[PDB]
Image 1 (cartoon, rainbow over the protein chains, first blue to last red):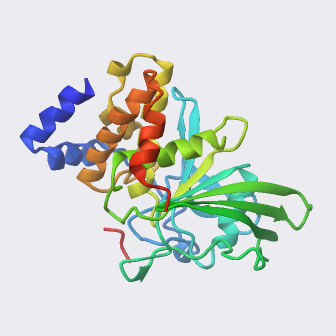
Image 2: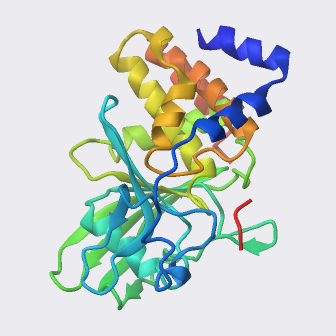
Image 3: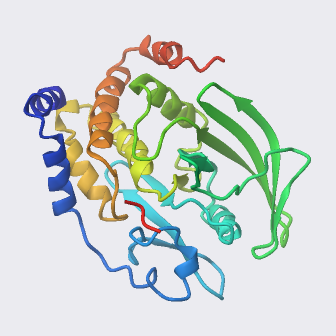
Length: 298
Length: 4
C-alpha cells in the first residue's frame, strides 16, 4: 500500500535516502553519440544526455543527433519522448523530430526564462501574425489560437512541411508555474493539468509519442511521466496495490538518465498518484474538485 | 553549464 509506505517515509524522514537509493540502482548505459564533439553544441547541459539505445534519431543524412529519448513502457502501453529545452540552433531539429515521430502533443513544464537565466529557446511563435520558418529542416510553424489559464496555457499550433505541403495540428500544453527543481503548488493543479492533456487525445496510441520537455528534460519531465504511467497501470491491472512507484521510476531510468531530480519531486509523485488514484477507482466528483482547487480561472 |  502506497499510503502505508508514504506515511512510513514521512515519519522516518528518509526521503533523501529512498531517493538516493534510486540514484544508486539507476541504470547506466553508454552515451557514445551524445558525447561526440560534433554534437557538443546540441547539448544544453553536460551531465544530461540520451542513451544510444533509446535516443531519438533524426531522419536526415547530415547529423542525426538530438537530445531526446524514447521512453517506452511496454506493460503500460504508452510511450513518451523526453528532450531538453531546445537550444536556439536545434529548434528546427526539435520540430523535425515532432513531425517524423508523428507527435500531436508537446508538454512544456518550464518557462523560457527562469530565475534570471535563459532555460529554453523561444521555439514557438507568440503571435498568430508571426509564424516561424525553420530553413534547416524546411518547416513552418504558425500560431492558431491559445487558451490562457492562470498557471497553464494551451496553444493550438499548425506545423507544415514545406517540402511536401502536408500540415498537422499540434497542441502545446505549457505549465508556467513549476519551478526548476521544485514542485507544483498542489496535486490538484498538477492532475488538472495531466487530464487536460489526456482528454485532448495527444496521449492516444493512434498518434506518435507525446513530446515532454523542461530545461534538461529529466526533472519536472520524469515527474509528469511517472504519475501518468502509474495511473495508467492502476486502471489496467485494476489492482492498485500492485503499483510500486520505486520500481516504475527505475524502469524509466533505463531509457533516460536522471529522471526526477530532487527527493521532494519524488515525494510529490507519490501524493499525485495517491490523489489521482481516486479517479481511477471511480470517483467522478474529483474530476471537478481538482479544477476548482487549481484556480485555473483567472 | 551543468544541470545540478
